[PDB]
Structures are given as structure tokens and as C-alpha cells.
Image (cartoon, rainbow, N blue to C red):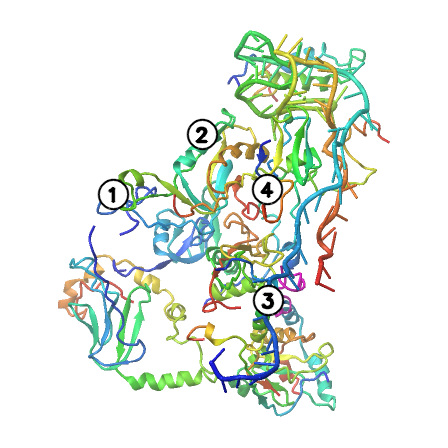
RNA sequence: UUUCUAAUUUUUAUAUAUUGAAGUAAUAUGUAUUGAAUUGAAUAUUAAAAAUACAAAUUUAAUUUGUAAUUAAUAAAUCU
């Protein structure tokens, strides 16, 4: 069938076979507008105001850039990863040289609107400003392929971020 | 009761105060889905309506983080858990819903040729979700305050749910005074499109 | 990898609500042999005067009469097919129910109303959730066999334990 | 194909359309009669 | 017990103000750090 | 680019010109009272040689058989002939000077029918007394 | 926050004498009144880790004279 | 058919002690006088080095 | 005259005059 | 002079870095670091036409 | 598309500036502390101490000097 016996929601694994489930292309389509806002608990978080498909390598290159522009001892970046992953070039004639093994391996997320990505969470009484915050994320936002805006602590008040 | 035929939803007295649509709040009786409710009676957020709980129940305060707050359900609270439910039923209905359209769009700018009216959102609220409101509360975005909605694809616009202060309703909904109704304008030829 | 056959159409061969002869297949159900294994549960279980064919799970009525689907009050996914034998009993009411509601004199809280059944049961039996949710102790489910010989209980039924309402 | 924009006069004479329909359905919600 | 839509519901056609370049400081505060809209490629929204 | 061709009473219009406020004022008139003198003034409107019945009863047809009040020739309107607007062809011209009344079985329907009137541009009606107009037999 | 430990103690009785040789207007020895001058040297101390006793601690300087009351 | 509709008001429409914080960093228009601020010309503030050093 | 008119009440129906403003061949088979 | 792709990216790096209307294009011109910190908004060439650059 | 005629859908639709705000003054916990060859608001990290307002810079091997001192500048008023 289709999703069950998940591997902790990263990707679904076939019930009668440990193979990955190999879903449809437009499964889990991000082209909703997510109704549920995110209750971020970091001081600032980077939510995705639009939708798209973002790799893990695009999200890891962004962390390596956010982790440069951030004061070390004070704030510890927090990157969320519980979201579900999705496959790539999977099909057989649709792969190159019958190497379906080396094309599906990439795992990209289908982010809807308003999913938090990172967190400049605090480890002290040190504080942040939106100017002090957007300045950090302005490095990584140039890698995350979709549009994203930073949001302050607590419930994103999506009346304003949009 | 049978393993085949199970109640699709069951009655529930909430002890805690869950945010989600299936959620409730302190002490109201709600028929929430079975699978969800069954991981509440284990979780402790809910308890099946025994005759005892129908008078009082020890609800929860995040202040001391334990089931101390006794919320007695006299006929007065049962006039409070109604207006507070009837309110956040309009909330969780428009916020969960994704109201569709079919419109005509000759031209290139992907522009709906007869753009939308705040009449034409309360009309697709009452049509699809039966949510009956005043179209004087629907505030549009800044891009569509001038020309109406006017563009295909996903538009959203804010619906103002005014009367939520004597219900003591905050932190159990995303925004006390608004809600994002989420349009979508699926262009269609004269066959299925109106206006 | 392989091929596949086309999924046949397993749908109604009458109009629900309208009269019905016995030689009509009321519904040709998927004997949902998941893939030709031997265990399935049909969508529309048989009802009054309707008898299910064992092999292909197709419901054939047993007596000519008007037909209807009774969605279970507990779970609206599990339906029966009722055939009530008297065709005049419903026609001579429909012709009224649809003549009254034309003059605006019929009430919409009728049991047969589709959207009211959720509330209808609750006006009469207010705790029916608890009457089906109640779990029975294995003592009362097998009432004292001596009460059967002493004749107190008319006849012990130990397997009929599930409330199908 | 839909290449150049709908001329403005057309959009305007199509805003008269929805304001025709918005004037039909004002007729199709009148009472069936009038107590006179 | 009256709610007037008009108090809180404001539908104002606001002029999107230019980032004032004629003054130096108000050009720097106005620098809304979302000018990295350059990631607006209409990229593949359901594939990679 | 609407609101340039059409007014502001376009797109910013809550076309629900039916009942954003009147329903409230309906429950206002419900509160105060209606009594003998409040019918005795209407009695003078029956004393007025010009006979247009003042009060109207929106009650089920079996109810009125039980307590017939039709004596002063008052109007018996089904509460939908009021709501639907089928009654405007028999309704006073002076929308600002006329105050009819509305009798009803239980006072929820009365106010629920008088709000329909105030939706039809009517200004004064205190909207109920099932028992007074019988105690004021006239 | 750089070092993890309060360094050498002090007591307000001592800052009042560091504050006596530190007068901004050495023409007007007390332009800032002395008590106002101390909160300055106290803050500069705390900013160096100098936890003084009268504050920063649960108990003030214990005395063999009398009850805490 | 169910129709969902708001309850009748018993208290103030816009919440006051229930208001969610605004949601945008509340750097007021007066701490960084970015725009929308109007001041009398007699009462011009904060020119401590330009034209408040010689106040009138 | 400030009075709900009093008299034996006749009710009168309505008669719609319908015209066709859009071509029929653009629309569905039900319309 | 690196065309700062939108107008909004323009930033005055130096004290002598100011704005200028170089033929309808808002640009940044600095006497110091003359081309090192110079920025020019993206816009049509100063002398375009209606058939060549739309 | 019988023929003469009449007609309500038109290779005509509105494009972002006014203002290189650059004079107006010695100082004073203080060159904090730490890490540092050195660092004095502008190395590195560290940032909720204060009082008698000006610690996210340029500058210098360091400082001082020297730039800088949170302001009027309403395109909205459709143009037909
Ligand atoms: Zn420069």
C-alpha cells in the first residue's frame, strides 16, 4: 500500500518489505497554505512563508552559514528535522544507466507555509533584536531555496509575517 | 463495541485544555474522534462522562502544572461552555477549511477578471462550510484591499471573530481575534465557471 | 515489473429508496479478498429481508419491496440494506410527505431526514453511547447456566455479545 | 493562447456581468407572492 | 453588546513607501532584510 | 482596479444589510414591557375611525384556535410572510411614525418576527404581549 | 560570565573608601554625593566579579553583636 | 444541516487582557523615528550636538 | 396611515419575464 | 560597478559613499575607493529604445 | 451561411521623483575586566553593572585628534 509502518515519519517503509515506500511525485504536496502556526520556543526562528521542496544538503549548507554569523557561547542554533522526507529521480527508465540506487538516495522535504526551520535559542540572559536576528539569518536565507522570514519567540502571529 | 464496528467518535470530558480542533477545554463535554480520544483517556486530558464528572472535574492550570483546579459544571458553566464552544467552532471550522473557487480568467496576468468581493467570501463561507458571518468583518490583505482578491491560486484573507474576551479564550487558539480563511481560485472555462 | 488487470465496477444495480424485485442484484460488492486470500468484510452488510450470497458477496433481496440503506448509528461507515416489503406503505406516504412539504406543512425533523439522524437518536435514547460503549464483565455475559435450567432466562446466548446499533 | 491582456473595456463590461447576476439573484429571493 | 466592524477591521489602500534613499539613517533601518527575495525562481514546487 | 469605478460602498461592503444591529434592538424592546396602556394607546388606534389593525399575531394556526384574539380584526400573519417580505404590501406607510405590535406564542418568536420588521425599515415596535392583548380584550 | 566564579569578596564598607579617593570634580570633592558615587564603584566591581557581601548573598555580614532582627 | 455561527456578545469585542502580543518587534516609532512621527517645530527633540546645544 | 392595512387579504403571485443574454452553446448539458 | 540586482540592496559602505541619479538609475558613487565600493541599481541602459530593451 | 437590410464585444488604457539634513563641542568610573606582543567604545569573547546620556563603526601598531549627532520635505487628489 501507502504510508504505514513509518520509519519515525522521516520516510514511510513498505509494510511487508523494508524497502522505502516510493511515493507519488505530488504526494504530501506543499501547495497547501498551512493553517497551523508554529509555536517556536527559540528566541527567533526561521519559518518558511512560502512552500517548496528543500533538500537536506541545502538545509545543511544553510546551518553552516548561520553558525558563522552567530555569537558562540551565548546562542546555540537549533535545527528542526522531525519533518517528513521525500524521494527523487526514483523510477527505472527515468534513472540514468539503470542506476536507480544512486538517484533516489537524495532526500528532500516538502515544506508548506510557515514551518520553522532553525532557532536562535538562548543559553543565557543575553537578548536579541530583530535587526540582530535578521542579520544572522541573512546568510542562510540566501541558500534555502524558498522564501523565508524570521519570527520572534512564541506563537508566530501570522497576521504580520504575511 | 465489536472490533469491526467501533464508535467513530465518543463522548469526552476534557480535563486539560487542548489547542487542536478535536481539542476542547476545561470541563466541556465533546464527542471527539475515537482514535484521538483514546490517546486522551490514557493521557489524562479527558475522562469518559461518568455520572460523577457531570458535576465537577479537576481541570488543569499551567501555573502549578497539576490537576488541582476544580471546575464545577453547574447550569451557569453550561451556558459558558456553549458560547465558548459555539465560538471556537466557527474558528476551527474556517481555519481548518480551504474554500475553493471556479472563475474565468481570460488574459495573461493570471488575473481573475471579475475580482472577489467580501460578499463573495461570506458567500463561499456559507456555501461550503455553512459558516454564517458578517462580511463586514472580513479584512483583506494589503495587495487586495484595492481591487478585491483578483488573482488565481492561493489567496487568504482575515476573518475577525470579535466577541472573544468574556469567554477567556486565548492560548487555546492561534489568534484570539482573527482567523485566516484560505481561498483558492481554480480557473475554469464557461462550462463550469460563473460570473 | 509486470502487468495488471482492470478493476471491475462493483456498484449498485438498483436505485436505493425505490422498489425492488428479488432477481435484482441489490449491490455487487467487493468480496474484498485483499488479493484472493480468504478474509473480507463487505461494505454493505445484509439487512431486513436481504440475504447475501456467500460466494460473491452480492446482496439479493428475498421479497419484492422498496429498498433502502441503513447507515449504522454507531459508525456511519457500516451500512445495511433494508428491503421493507410493502411498496404501498411507503409510496402512499411519500406522496403525502412530498405533498405536505410542498404546502410547507411538513416538519424536517423526520427520522428519514439524512442530516437529522445524528440528533434523532439522541432525543429518545440520550445515553446510547454508554449502552454500546459499556464493556460487559465475563460473569453477566454467560449468565448462570443454572438460571437456564431453572428457566429464569429464556435461553442463554453466549456469543451474541456485540451491540450492532 | 492567452498572450496579451484582456483589453480593459472587456474587464469593465464584465464587471457589469457579475453586477447583472448580483441583480438576478436579488429577484430570485423575493417572496413567491405578496399579501395584498 | 455591539461590535463595530469599522474599529478593528481597517481596509486602507496604503501606499507602499519607498525605502528613503535621500536620508542616510532611515535608509539603513528601512533595510528590511528580506531583499533576499532573489530566491523567488518559481522553482519546482513538487520535485527536485 | 475596483473602488475606482465603483464606490467605496463596493468591495468594502458588507452586503449583509439585513441584521447587524436591528436584531439587538429587537431584544431591547423585548426587555422593557407592554401592558394595558401600551394597548390602550393602540385602542385609540382602534378608536381612530380609520381601521387598519395595529397589532399582529405570529402564532401557529392551532394555537390561535385555542385563544382566539381575532376580535378587533387584527392581522394574523404567518411569521414567514413577515420574514420573507410578503407582508410589505400591507404595512403602514409612515415607517418612522407607526408602531404596530407583534403578539406571539412564546416571546422568542415575537422578537424574532419584530426584528424582521425592523429589517424592513420599521422603527418602533415593542414587540410582545401574548397575554395583555387578551386582558385588553379590545 | 567569562570566568564562571565570583572572585575575591568585598563589603559595602570597603567601597565607601574606594569612593572617597575617587571624586570627579577634584575642585568640588563631593559633586556626586558619596552614596551616589558608591553605586558606581559597586557596579564596576560586580562587573569584575567582586561579589560584595551586603548584597549578592543570602545573608549580610554576620556580627557577634546581636540577633539578625 | 449544521450551520456554524458566532455567539452573541456579552463583553468587549476586541480583547484587552486577552490580546496576543502584537507579533512584530515593538521597536516603537519613537525609539527609532523611522516614519509617521509628527512633532511641533518649537518642540524639536534631541539635537544635543546640533541645535539643542544652544536651545533657543 | 401608520396602520397595518385591514381587509380580506388576497395574495398575488409573480410572473418572471426571462430573456437569454449569453449564448447557450458555451455552457454545459445541464444548463 | 557591480549592479546590485535590486535597488533595495544598495548600501553605503563608506562615509563618502552617497546616492546619485545617474540617468534615472539610483546608484552609489564614492570619491574614495572609486570603483571598489561603487554600486549601480539594475535598470535599462541610459539610452534605450522601445524595440531594443522594451 | 438563399439575396437585400438592420447590430450591443473597440490590433486607444494612466509608467514613482521634492531632500550629496554633513555648523552649533576640552576633559571627569574607564585606557573596564578577561584573552591577549599590543587593543584605550570600532583585535578576539563578553555583554542586561553604572552615573552627571550617546560601547553593534571609520581611524591608529596603540590612543588622542577627526567624520557622525534618532526630522518637515504628504506622487495619495482616478482620470475622463
Ligand atoms: Zn565606500
Tag 2 secondary structure: helix
Q: Nearer the viewer, mark 3 or mark 4?
A: 3
Residue placed under numbered mark 3 in the picture: D15
Is most of the magenta stretch helix, strand or loop? loop
Label drawn at residue A64: 2
Labels 1 and 2: the sequence-earlier one: 1
The chain identifier of the residue carrying mark 1 reads A
Label drawn at residue E10: none
Q: Nearer the viewer, mark 3 or mark 2?
A: 3
**Disc 2 from disc 4: Cα separation:** 27 Å
Tag 1 secondary structure: loop
Query: 10 Å neighbourhood of mark 4: few (<14), some, or many (≥20)?
Result: some
Q: Residue at x 35, y 40 (%)?
A: A107
**Disc 1 from disc 2: Cα separation:** 32 Å
Ligand 1 under 8 Å from disc 4 Cβ: no
Q: Which residues are magenta?
A: F1-23
**Disc 3 from disc 1: Cα separation:** 56 Å
Residue I27, percent from left and from top = 46, 72
Quarter for ligand 1? Answer: top right
In this rendered view, identify the residue nearer to me: A123 or E30.
E30
**Disc 3 from disc 4: Cα separation:** 38 Å
Label drawn at residue H24: 4
Q: Are marks 4 and 1 on the same chain?
A: no
Residue placed under numbered mark 1 in the picture: A19
Tag 4 secondary structure: loop
**F10 inside magenta stretch:** yes
Amino acid at each position: 500500500l501507502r504510508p504505514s509502518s513509518l520509519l519515525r515519519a522521516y520516510h514511510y517503509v513498505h509494510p511487508k518489505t523494508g524497502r522505502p515506500i516510493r511515493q507519488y511525485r505530488k504526494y504530501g504536496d506543499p501547495r497547501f497554505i498551512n493553517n497551523e502556526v508554529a509555536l517556536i520556543k527559540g528566541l527567533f526562528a526561521l519559518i518558511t512563508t512560502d512552500f517548496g521542496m528543500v533538500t537536506q544538503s541545502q538545509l545543511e549548507n544553510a546551518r553552516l552559514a548561520i553558525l558563522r554569523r552567530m555569537p558562540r557561547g551565548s546562542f546555540a542554533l537549533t535545527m528542526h528535522t522531525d519533518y517528513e522526507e521525500f524521494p527523487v529521480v526514483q523510477k527505472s527508465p527515468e534513472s540514468r544507466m539503470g542506476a536507480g540506487k544512486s538517484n533516489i538516495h537524495h532526500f528532500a522535504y516538502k515544506f508548506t507555509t510557515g514551518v520553522p526551520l532553525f532557532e536562535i535559542t538562548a543559553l543565557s540572559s543575553r537578548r536579541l533584536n530583530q535587526a540582530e536576528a535578521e542579520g544572522i539569518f541573512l546568510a542562510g536565507r540566501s541558500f534555502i531555496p524558498l522564501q523565508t522570514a524570521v519570527v520572534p519567540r512564541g506563537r508566530v502571529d501570522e497576521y504580520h509575517v504575511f | 463495541m465489536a472490533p469491526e464496528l467501533q464508535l467513530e467518535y465518543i463522548p469526552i470530558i476534557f480535563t486539560r485544555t487542548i489547542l487542536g480542533p478535536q481539542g476542547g477545554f476545561a470541563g466541556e463535554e465533546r464527542l471527539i474522534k475515537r482514535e484521538v480520544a483514546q490517546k486522551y483517556m490514557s493521557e489524562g486530558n479527558a475522562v469518559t462522562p461518568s455520572a460523577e464528572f457531570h458535576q465537577g472535574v479537576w481541570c488543569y492550570n499551567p501555573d502549578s502544572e497539576q490537576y488541582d483546579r476544580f471546575v464545577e459544571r453547574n447550569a451557569e458553566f453550561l451556558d459558558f461552555a456553549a458560547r465558548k464552544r459555539q465560538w471556537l467552532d466557527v474558528y476551527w471550522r474556517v481555519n481548518t477549511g480551504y474554500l475553493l473557487f471556479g472563475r474565468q480568467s481570460w488574459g495573461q496576468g493570471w488575473l481573475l477578471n471579475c475580482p472577489l468581493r467580501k460578499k463573495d467570501i461570506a458567500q463561499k463561507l456559507w456555501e461550503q462550510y455553512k459558516v454564517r458571518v458578517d462580511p463586514r468583518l472580513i479584512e483583506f490583505r494589503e495587495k487586495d484591499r484595492r481591487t478585491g482578491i483578483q488573482d488565481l491560486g492561493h489567496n487568504w484573507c482575515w476573518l475577525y471573530l470579535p466577541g472573544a474576551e468574556e469567554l477567556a479564550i486565548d492560548r487555546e487558539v492561534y489568534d484570539n481575534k482573527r482567523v485566516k480563511v484560505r481561498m483558492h481560485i481554480r480557473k475554469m472555462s464557461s462550462y463550469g465557471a460563473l460570473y | 515489473q509486470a502487468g495488471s488487470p482492470r478493476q471491475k465496477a462493483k456498484l449498485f444495480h438498483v436505485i436505493p429508496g425505490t422498489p425492488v424485485t428479488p432477481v435484482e442484484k441489490l449491490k455487487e460488492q467487493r468480496r474484498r479478498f485483499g488479493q484472493d486470500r480468504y478474509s473480507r468484510q463487505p461494505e454493505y452488510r445484509p439487512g431486513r429481508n436481504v440475504r447475501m450470497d456467500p460466494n460473491t458477496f452480492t446482496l439479493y433481496a428475498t421479497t419484492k419491496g422498496v429498498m433502502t440503506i441503513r447507515t449504522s448509528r454507531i459508525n456511519p461507515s457500516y451500512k445495511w440494506l433494508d428491503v421493507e416489503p410493502d411498496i404501498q406503505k411507503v409510496y402512499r406516504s411519500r406522496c403525502m410527505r412530498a405533498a405536505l412539504q410542498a404546502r410547507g406543512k411538513a416538519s424536517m425533523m423526520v427520522a428519514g431526514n439524512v442530516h437529522y439522524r445524528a440528533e434523532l437518536d439522541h432525543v429518545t435514547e440520550p445515553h446510547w453511547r454508554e449502552r454500546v460503549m459499556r464493556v460487559p464483565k465475563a460473569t453477566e455475559r454467560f449468565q448462570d447456566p443454572n438460571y437456564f435450567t431453572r428457566g429464569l432466562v429464556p435461553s442463554l446466548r453466549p456469543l451474541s455479545r456485540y451491540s450492532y446499533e | 493562447e492567452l498572450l496579451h491582456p484582456l483589453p480593459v473595456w472587456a474587464r469593465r463590461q464584465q464587471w457589469l456581468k457579475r453586477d447583472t447576476v448580483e441583480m438576478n439573484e436579488a429577484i430570485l429571493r423575493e417572496p413567491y407572492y405578496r399579501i395584498k | 453588546a455591539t461590535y463595530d466592524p469599522a474599529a478593528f477591521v481597517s481596509d486602507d489602500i496604503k501606499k507602499d513607501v519607498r525605502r528613503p534613499f535621500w536620508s542616510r539613517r532611515r535608509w539603513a533601518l528601512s533595510d528590511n532584510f528580506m531583499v533576499p527575495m532573489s530566491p523567488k525562481p518559481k522553482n519546482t514546487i513538487k520535485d527536485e | 482596479n475596483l473602488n475606482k469605478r465603483y464606490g467605496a460602498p463596493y468591495v468594502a461592503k458588507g452586503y449583509a444589510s439585513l441584521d447587524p444591529r436591528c436584531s439587538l434592538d429587537a431584544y431591547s424592546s423585548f426587555q422593557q414591557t407592554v401592558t394595558s396602556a401600551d394597548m390602550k394607546k393602540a385602542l385609540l388606534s382602534i378608536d381612530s375611525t380609520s381601521s387598519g389593525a395595529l397589532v399582529i399575531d405570529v402564532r401557529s394556526e392551532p394555537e390561535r384556535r385555542l385563544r382566539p384574539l381575532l376580535s378587533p380584526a387584527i392581522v394574523a400573519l404567518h411569521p414567514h410572510d413577515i420574514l420573507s417580505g410578503a407582508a410589505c404590501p400591507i404595512l403602514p406607510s409612515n415607517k418612522e411614525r407607526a408602531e404596530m405590535f407583534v403578539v406571539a406564542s412564546e416571546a422568542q418568536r415575537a422578537v424574532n418576527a419584530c426584528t424582521a420588521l425592523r429589517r424592513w425599515g420599521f422603527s418602533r415596535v415593542t414587540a410582545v404581549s401574548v397575554d395583555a392583548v387578551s386582558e385588553a380584550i379590545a | 560570565v567569562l570566568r564562571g566564579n565570583y572572585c575575591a569578596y568585598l563589603t559595602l564598607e570597603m567601597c565607601y573608601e574606594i569612593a572617597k579617593m575617587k571624586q570627579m570634580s577634584w575642585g568640588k570633592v563631593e559633586y556626586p554625593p558619596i552614596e551616589v558615587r558608591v553605586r558606581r564603584v559597586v557596579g564596576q566591581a560586580r562587573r569584575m566579579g567582586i561579589a560584595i557581601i551586603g548584597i549578592d548573598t543570602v545573608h549580610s555580614s554576620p556580627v557577634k553583636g546581636m540577633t539578625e532582627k | 444541516e449544521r450551520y456554524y455561527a458566532l455567539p452573541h456578545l456579552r463583553g468587549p469585542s476586541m480583547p484587552v487582557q486577552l490580546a496576543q502580543p502584537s507579533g512584530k518587534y515593538p521597536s516603537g516609532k519613537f525609539t527609532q523615528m523611522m516614519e509617521d512621527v509628527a512633532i511641533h517645530p518649537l518642540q524639536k527633540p534631541d539635537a544635543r550636538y546640533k541645535h539643542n546645544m544652544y536651545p533657543a | 396611515t401608520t396602520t397595518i392595512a385591514a381587509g380580506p387579504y388576497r395574495r398575488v403571485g409573480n410572473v418572471f419575464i426571462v430573456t437569454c443574454i449569453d449564448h447557450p452553446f458555451k455552457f454545459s448539458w445541464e444548463v | 560597478h557591480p549592479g546590485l540586482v535590486p535597488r533595495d540592496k544598495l548600501k553605503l559602505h563608506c562615509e563618502f559613499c552617497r546616492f546619485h541619479w545617474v540617468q534615472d538609475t539610483l546608484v552609489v558613487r564614492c570619491a574614495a575607493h572609486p570603483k571598489e565600493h561603487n554600486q549601480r541599481e539594475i535598470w535599462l541602459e541610459p539610452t534605450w529604445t522601445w524595440g531594443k530593451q522594451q
